[PDB]
Image (cartoon, rainbow, N blue to C red):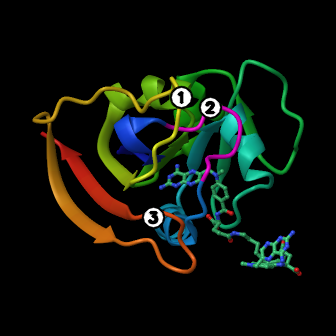
Amino acid sequence: MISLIAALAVDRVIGMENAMPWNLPADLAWFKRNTLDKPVIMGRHTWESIGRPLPGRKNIILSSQPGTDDRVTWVKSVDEAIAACGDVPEIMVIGGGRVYEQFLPKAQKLYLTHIDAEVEGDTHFPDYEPDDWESVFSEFHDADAQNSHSYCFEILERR
Ligand SMILES: CN(Cc1cnc2nc(N)nc(N)c2n1)c1ccc(C(=O)N[C@@H](CCC(=O)NCCCCCCCCCNC(=O)CC[C@H](NC(=O)c2ccc(N(C)Cc3cnc4nc(N)nc(N)c4n3)cc2)C(=O)O)C(=O)O)cc1
Ligand SMILES: [Cl-]
């Protein structure tokens, strides 16, 4: 089973290359808890933004270009990425936008953090249809001394 996990600004704007304009360690904690001990599939921009292998996860980077870090696994196609994950209960696809578009048709679950941040940009999380998905968890948090913006964790399961 393949899941996508993403942090979305208003109107589902997501990162394209430069770091997103927020400071959300609680979102990073949610990401770490929902991805640890699972293989993670990412594109090259997300890899650069992470800046290091994510510990405790097989890191798989989908890129047309040769790999530049032997600490992680480099693949050139979607099927190669899935194969590198091997036989596990859940694959976490962690972005960026082209990777989400590639994997959404295969995915059964979305972990979304909806962030109340007005971020300008043309890159968006792919369209999902409101009703093709069951929202099974939702939990709101206000901005605080450590987190710049309010944020709502949601888990959806494909109908
Ligand atoms: C891009 N992505 C992709 C991404 C992101 N989010 C997503 N979210 C979702 N939902 N989904 C996705 N797919 C998704 N993808 C991802 C995905 C995952 C991850 C990922 O890491 N994750 C880890 C978990 C976290 C972790 O483990 N993260 C990090 C791990 C390392 C932590 C160990 C600490 C080592 C020390 C290093 N320390 C430092 O550098 C700071 C230096 C230090 N200072 C401070 O500390 C400090 C602080 C506050 C301060 N202030 C307030 C007051 C202040 C401020 N600024 C000032 N500036 C000026 N001039 N003047 C001031 N007076 C001033 N005052 C002042 C000073 C020091 O002075 O010594 C993990 O998944 O294991 C990352 C990216
Ligand atoms: Cl990417």
Image x and y of residue 12, in percent: 39, 37
Per the rendered image, the range of residues in magenta is 14-21
Image x and y of residue 41, in percent: 58, 41
Q: Identify the residue shown where x is 60% and y is 21%.
A: 77
Main secondary-structure element of the magenta-colored stretch = loop
CA distance separating discs 1 and 2: 8 Å
Towards the viewer: 28 or 115: 115
Q: Amino acid at mark 2?
A: Met
CA distance separating discs 1 and 3: 27 Å
Say what secondary structure mark 2 lies in: loop
Placement of the N terminus among the 4 image quadrants: top left
Say what secondary structure mark 3 lies in: helix
Placement of the C terminus among the 4 image quadrants: top left
On residue 16, the disc is 2
Q: Amino acid at mark 3?
A: Asn
**Is residue 88 visible in the rendered structure shown here?**
yes
Residue 45, quarter of picture: top right
Quarter of image, ligand 2: top right
Disc on the earlier residue, 2 or 3: 2
